Image (cartoon, rainbow, N blue to C red; front, side, top):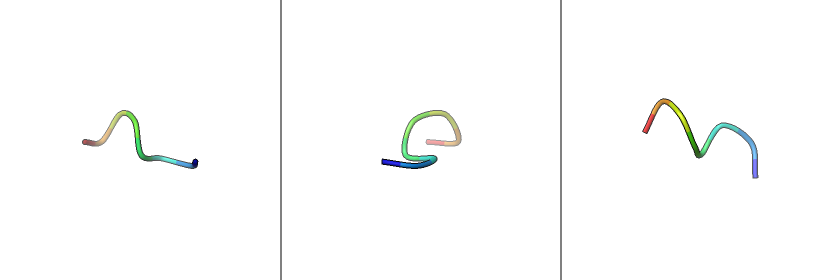
Length: 8
């Protein structure tokens, strides 16, 4: 994916 892990 990309950044779809943490900042969520």
